[PDB]
Length: 49
Length: 82
Image (cartoon, rainbow over all chains, first blue to last red; front, side, top):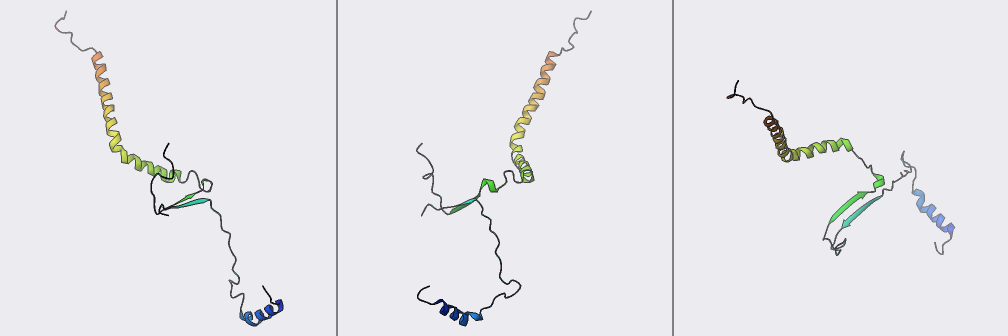
């Protein structure tokens, strides 16, 4: 963002980021898994502080 | 009454973890480990609890036996005869 034209940024990315690769192997793009919230309580009682 | 949480004692470098009561079973491994626990607890005290009360039953089983024997008549009919 700034005083830059979108065409210049796209062309610059095409020049340098074209060497980047995707879908490397069977993993390709890994997917996330849900994380379960757990009602709990942690108490680090330190009276010095 | 001049004593509440905040000034009870000085506790340092102790971390505690706990779970929500709704995220854990109220009766977890009740008979799986509770029953083997009670056997452990009973043995740890049966050598200091049972002998004092075992003696009382021995007193019971003898103090009551002698009482009926006193009420029972004894064969002391001699020296009178016919």
